[PDB]
Amino acid sequence: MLIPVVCFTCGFPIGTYAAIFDKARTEYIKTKMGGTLPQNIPLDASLQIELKDLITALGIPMRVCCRTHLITTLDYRKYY
Amino acid sequence: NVDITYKDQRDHTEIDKLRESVQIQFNFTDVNIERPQHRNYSQGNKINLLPNKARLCGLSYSGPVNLAAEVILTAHYSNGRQEVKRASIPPFQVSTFPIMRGSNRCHTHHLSKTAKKEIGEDPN
Amino acid sequence: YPRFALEAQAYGFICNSYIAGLTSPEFIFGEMNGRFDLINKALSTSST
Amino acid sequence: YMTTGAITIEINSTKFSKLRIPWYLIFRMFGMTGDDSIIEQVVFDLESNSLVNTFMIEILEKSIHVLDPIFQPVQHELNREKIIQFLSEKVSKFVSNPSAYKSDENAVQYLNERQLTILDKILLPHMGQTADTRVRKLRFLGLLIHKILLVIMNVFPPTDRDSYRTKRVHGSGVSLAKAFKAIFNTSVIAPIINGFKELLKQTAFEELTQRNIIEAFSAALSKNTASDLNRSMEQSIISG
Amino acid sequence: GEMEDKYKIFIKNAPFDPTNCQIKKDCPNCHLDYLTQICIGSQKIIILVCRCGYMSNRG
Amino acid sequence: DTGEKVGMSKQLAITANVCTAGEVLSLKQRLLSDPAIQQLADVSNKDIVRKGLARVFINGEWIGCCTNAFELAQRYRMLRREGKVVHPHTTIYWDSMVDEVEFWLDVGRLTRPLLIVDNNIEKYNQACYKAAEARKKGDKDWEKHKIPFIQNTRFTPQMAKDILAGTLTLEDLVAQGICEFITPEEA
Ligand SMILES: [Zn+2]
Ligand SMILES: [Zn+2]
């Protein structure tokens, strides 16, 4: 229901940066879109923004697993 | 619109011996459907039955149906003369018909995503 | 495909490999072929 | 269509039960008796001498010369009314005492009118239910026979039982209605009939007033009817 | 046989059915660039029909 | 995938819907009013096989005969694209093998929207005709009167962008004749 405390695969503490990563990510996407209605922002276009440098700025390594689970984990607070 | 004839077999008076059969005829006048309701057990009216309440209590999410009718009968004698009677029935709760979830007859039609989420329904 | 089509594609010739990706007509023909094998495998239990 | 050559018609419905009538009698009851007109009701022409039309008249001419055990004395009959009379002789379930209602005049007309109106509504009801639509019901039934003989002809394939140009998907509303009514038949009007039966069996009808009509109507619709109807409707939905 | 009544209606309607196979071949009657090809029967008889009424095999 | 249930429980495709029942009476009273239809009681079987008239069914029942079945079916198809005279969910089938027209507006018809392809076949045909006129008359450069054939859909990238932006709907595409609903009968 949230980004996990640790990476499911290796156990790196990805959760200690999860909250920040969420909020920062949102702001970052609002920079790349240019002030659009939340529905007029298509879902497929919000996912094509590269989050590589943002995750690196969080101090997270270049591990495939950690970034997979950080980027793709669904938050329940946005579905209910 | 039912219309049939049945042979009568009452043989006590002379006036009974003057008759042949009874012509049955009747129809229904006004039909309407209201939302599902519940009793709450206080000797009162019917209160709204929410879907989760029916899920939990093992009830049925059925709304009562209201019908009106007209019953007009004919009486046939031996000679060939007839006696016609008429009767009017006001709106009358016939039975409860099941209600589909999310339809016009459902309570979660006037209720939005927040309202569905608040009472114990799936908002999506 | 039009009526009385003479091209080989109209009757189930697939020019694409799986790694290249089939098209809609080729996927349908391959779906027709695959469904036959499932049905015959369903007759495997009952008939014998 | 049979191996011998007879072309027959069965009308499955509530009133009747799987009776098969040769393809000429249905046409003759409706006012079209001449054989040339009837062969123009299926082949649509008598002046085209091609393979299809020659073989069509061959099959249909051979069809009308078979002796069905049920329609022997009504095989070459000339008019409509006595054909309908024999129809009543056959299908009338409540008539089991022949040679008696024929001694009077009114019963013949009553049976003829009843069998005229039922077959006016029970045959091809999508074309109408009044007498003015009977004539074109003849033409449409002829067209159906023609289409069937074209498949006998090996000219067109039979109907594909799996293509979706001849399928429909109904769903909740239609099935719920047709089950709300199929069980309405047993638990409502039959109880009303029986309640009126037992009200007439006890209380004098010339003494019966409106109050007792209301009493009997609300008695025949007591909790047994409402219970049985809804229980059978839910049992039908859950049983499959 | 065929081409005569088993498919006469279909053949006459062929130049108008949009789902029929067209052939890049000139027409003699109306000098049209394309014709409609139909392959009927188990002998696979080929007929080139045109909207102008042209028909091969003397039709 | 296993057992006797294979091929028994089917699933709708992503764009497939099921049609409700349309107003059959409006279309029927429109058809009987159409001058290009001879009424069923106003024509006989001999007439319809002599001239070869084509019969017009609506929702199952036969309601007259037309002279040119293809022309009637395509004119009603063109009316269905305007959306005012014929309802967009009307099935208009034309059996060219037996030469009959069928209109359907009942319940249970699977439909899906399909983008409509147009072309300039009429301009191509007149160009071919004038090229033939110059061909037999003796012009050595007759073939520069011919025009290329063009077939295309009217769906543009801007319409896709607006669908993603929510400013365009399917009912707006049907309304301006870009897509139309097709049934397995009409397909
Ligand atoms: Zn990891
Ligand atoms: Zn031509």
Image (tube, coloured by chain):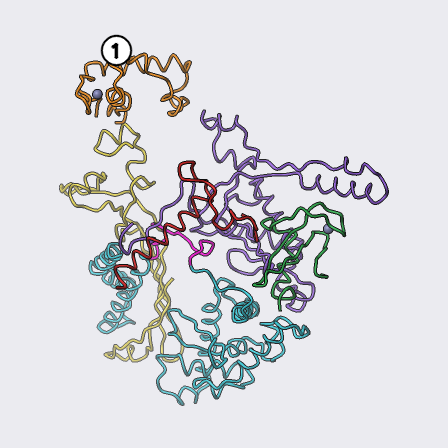
Residue A78 on image: x %, y %: 27, 24
| A69, above or below F53, in the image | above
- The chain identifier of the residue carrying mark 1 reads A
Q: Is residue D134 visible?
A: no
Who is closer to the viewer here, F179 or F131? F131
Nearer to the camera, D209 or F121:
F121
Residue numbers of the magenta segment: D162-178
Give the chain letter for purple: F
Which chain is in orange here? A
Chain with green colouring: E
| Viewport quadrant of the N terminus of chain A | top left
User: What residue do we see at 53% from left, 44% from top?
Assistant: F87
**Chain in cyan (letter):** D
Task: Report which residue position mark 1 lands on.
Answer: A58
Q: Secondary structure at mark 1?
A: loop
Q: Is D176 covered by the magenta stretch?
A: yes
| Chain C tint as drawn | red
Chain depicted in yellow: B
**Where residue C8 sits: x, y (%)?**
52, 48
The quarter of the image holding the C terminus of chain A is top left
Relative side of B102 to F63, left or right:
left
Indicate whether residue D127 is drawn in magenta: no
Residue neighbourhood size for the residue with mark 1, other residues' Cα within 10 Å, grouped as few (<14), some (14–19), many (≥20): some
